[PDB]
View (spheres, rainbow over the protein chains, first blue to last red):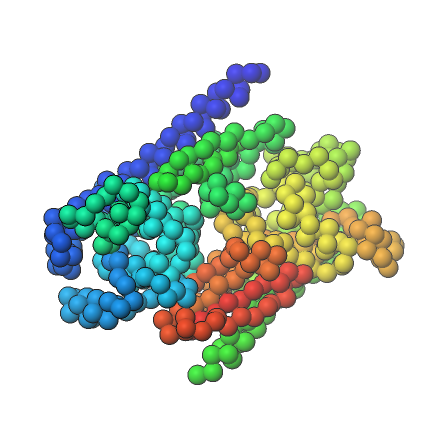
Length: 260
Length: 255
């Protein structure tokens, strides 16, 4: 009788480890994408050098579950016009600042993203115009760590609504102090980022997990889940659910499970 | 252009598509009515369902079925009858722990791929139960707040259930307690948020909309499009849509 809740605790702990392992495979390409801009130096990577970088990778094969990888530039309101004129001349003549919600602060604009054949065209999306993305960009900039958002709706990566996440990693200006969050924030020039759809990420890890009735949510708002699958055995409804806390990229996910 | 109008016609389209599903609810209840006092057989409900063509007649809805009201004391008896009437593998399936009165999915058509909600106790989940008791008390087709459709697709999708009650013949219906006491079951329709909206909106790229239920405006059940940068210098166009006892908040911007 007692062996049952231990045998399934083994099931849950392993499933939690797999979700966390898939999530942390994406970190590699995030640091690879920042690597390209570091190699480029102080003067932000050209369209040609970044597109050449992305073509040297094979994201569907190397990183199954991620839409792709890109670069967001940090630009103040008074430098928007010059940035847009520079970007337009570099191979994106139709690029414009695009807002997710009204924002008049400092803009964090998507400049590069590869590949379009995967998600959609997020070019010119102001990631600061939406608070959850802004909170992740700011936290990553201050910490120096890859920082995921709270669950979001991926606009620019197809329509209609597709639940997802963005994972951001800041690129620092060479020769600037990084000893404090504030020093690190003032040093950020842009961010390497990865957009990911909930469904695509989970498809790879738990292809056919008909042995579990699971639910996933962020701890900051447990009332709303971002993923749910299967119906539990009616016997397992006599006791409580197995819960696991998954720390992923500065965020905490709560995995709830029951057999069947 | 007149964008204020575009919104108004868009709202009318969403409501009108939602309100077409009511015909099938009354149709499914109507099959149950024709059988009489004794609950409809599996054969007669399936041949009623086969006399309908839900993808053509009602685009946007998953299908139509029947839920039976059964007390905890009568669970065993009810389950035996269903197992003998062509449902051998049926059992009370719970969405969450629940010890109260059971509202079990007896019939659903089309039981095509996915769509195996047979035995699903919709009373076991609060949003589904609230909609069912409100529908029974009012006598009106009543929808849930946004829900996750376990029993219709492997990774569960966002959706709604719309419920219409079945009353016992010869029982009074003047008060809501009278109506609730007379409730034998419900005709229901499960709905996917994506499927229903694909059927109304289509490939229109002229609007950047979002929908949420007024009970919780902090959570949208639908979002589509990126608005024109210019339109952000102004508030979005808003509209309240009365859908089966629920209020939807439509927020729209052009492009």
